[PDB]
Length: 39
Image: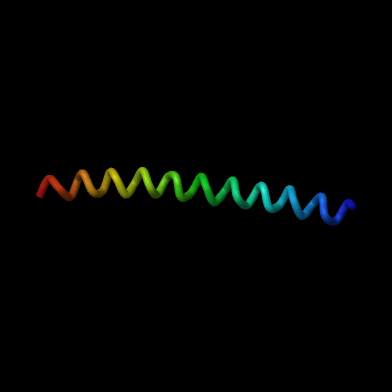
C-alpha cells in the first residue's frame, strides 16, 4: 500500500542519485589517469 509505494520511489530515487555519482566519478578517474600519465 501507501507505505510501500513511498518505499519503492525512495529506492528508485536513491539509486538514481548513486548511479549519477559513480558515473561522474568513473569519468573523473579516467580524466585523472590521463592527466597523470603526462608527468
